[PDB]
Amino acid sequence: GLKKMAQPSGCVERCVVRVCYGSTVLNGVWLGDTVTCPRHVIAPSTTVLIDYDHAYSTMRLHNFSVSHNGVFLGVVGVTMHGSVLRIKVSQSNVHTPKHVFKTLKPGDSFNILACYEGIASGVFGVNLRTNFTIKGSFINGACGSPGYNVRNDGTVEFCYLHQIELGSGAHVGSDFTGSVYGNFDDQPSLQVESANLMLSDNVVAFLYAALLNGCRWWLCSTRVNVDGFNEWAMANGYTSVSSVECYSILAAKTGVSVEQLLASIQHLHEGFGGKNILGYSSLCDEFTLAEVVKQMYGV
Amino acid sequence: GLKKMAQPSGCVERCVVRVCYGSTVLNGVWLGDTVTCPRHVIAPSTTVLIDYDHAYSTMRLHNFSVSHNGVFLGVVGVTMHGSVLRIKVSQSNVHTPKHVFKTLKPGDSFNILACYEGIASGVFGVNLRTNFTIKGSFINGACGSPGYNVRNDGTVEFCYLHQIELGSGAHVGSDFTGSVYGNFDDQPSLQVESANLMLSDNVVAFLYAALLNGCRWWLCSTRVNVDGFNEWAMANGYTSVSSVECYSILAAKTGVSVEQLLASIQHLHEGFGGKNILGYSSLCDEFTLAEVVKQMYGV
């Protein structure tokens, strides 16, 4: 069985703050004596292009208001790093978790804590897509909502700060160094993301989960090797497959090689007409190998 | 957009404890000076039918171990209430949230905090089906994982304790009074749940969500009234629709009457062939009216 789940949010909830500059309000993340938030908070109200260098030069500290659960924090200084601000505050968060900062790569799964006015409202798992966007559920005010992962030793990896929604509905964020994923602009514009590719590593994991649930009507006895599959994937909207050996735990429990699943992807690429696999009517790239193994075996 | 999300888990994480009796380990929920957990924890190791009254009669308090983050709570007394135990402990949980106990009805959405050995591992939203099961993701050791909702005023509604996985893969739990949802047996058996019905209320909410995203190819021009739909619903595996008055906010913005959606359900009852609605190839009863309203408008 497979369910997209989030890792527990409690340690991240204790870091979320409300950041206001003038009338503009969004979310930030308070670790130690630093609050990180999108620099959009200092943008002037205007319909023309934002000159953030100018806004930063004219910025005054007294225009900031930063609070955690309605308790206001004093602002000591502010510096700008790409698309984020680093706000130094006059006291440290006593609930700062053990943490690091990590930049995601396409195909990485992570957790979003959707926040509004410094208050978390929801949490869900997501995948960074090949076009460097995610499919979230955000409404007005979610800017600065953090993305995270929790390592096995309990270390929180801070990896995402929500920045903008594109005209297509795709969501764009930055890492905590201020680099926007996919090099999108952090202000309204007419930019469009590139076509989404199916995450082949995730589809292989999905088909192994199907096999382990007794669903195998689709299984191909043909084999396609990695080099051949990667050339096919180029022409058919799929990513390369990264490797084969990481699936050995599932290859052994089933009797099925990764190369058989690569052939099966090519066989199922257009549709199931009109059967289903684990309830899905087309191939699913929602679940990583790590998620399948964790949810099926606890590893 | 429509995404299944969970409400943040921090306030519930601080209530999960590890409950051990002999060698048997599961999860409990620590509120005030009471820990509630499934009575399965006192079951003998055997393949015969469990007599829980006899297990309770032979129980010894010193066989219990109850711990939070590796520190042990002194057990003072234990009573059995249906399928749960209420363990009195000598310390109160200083992180007990404002809370009530609520019994779910089919069609209700709630959050599951999946836990193992008293430690939370995942959080996800589920919906109670008409056969009083949920489709979660659990492996061995998840017994006692709590289900909750958080009210607008901050009150946590505790509504579910995970009990068993059926042969089908569906999951069964109890409420905090010890009543098993659907009155399934809380021990290994061959029980088969009745077939699920489509939750018509949730399908209506889902079609309102599609309208608000410009997805309208499926809208019937004609209408069916509630009485006519409910007659059809019996014959075709759908629940009766509750009322038309609830959807007025959706009926306003769209602005489509519930009767037009009920007619659309009748036409879309068979497949979409081969179109899709918000990515789905069939009607989705995953989302309640409250969820759609909260996710679209923050209310």
Image: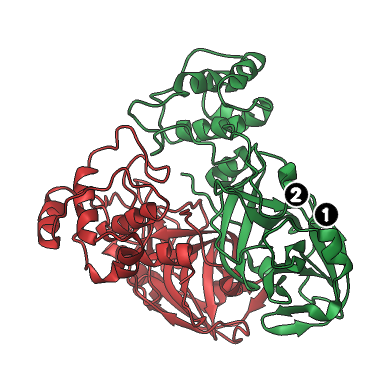
Chain colours: A green, B red
CB-based contact (under 8 Å), mark 1 and mark 2: yes
Q: CA distance from mark 1 to mark 2?
A: 8 Å
Q: In the rendered structure, which amino acid carries the disc numbered 2?
A: Val
Q: Is residue A95 above or below residue A213?
A: below
Nearest the viewer among B287 and A97 is: B287
Label 2 resides on the chain identified as A
Residue occupying the point 35% across, 55% down: B206
Q: In the rendered structure, which amino acid carries the disc numbered 1?
A: Gly
Q: Where residue A95 appears, x then y in whole percent?
A: 76, 74
Location of mark 1 (residue): A82
Location of mark 2 (residue): A180
Q: Where residue B255 appears, x then y in whole percent?
A: 31, 61
Q: Where residue A40 appears, x then y in whole percent?
A: 73, 63
Nearest the viewer among A131 and A273 is: A131
Q: Where residue A209 appears, x then y in whole percent?
A: 50, 36
Asked whether residue B190 is in view, the answer is yes
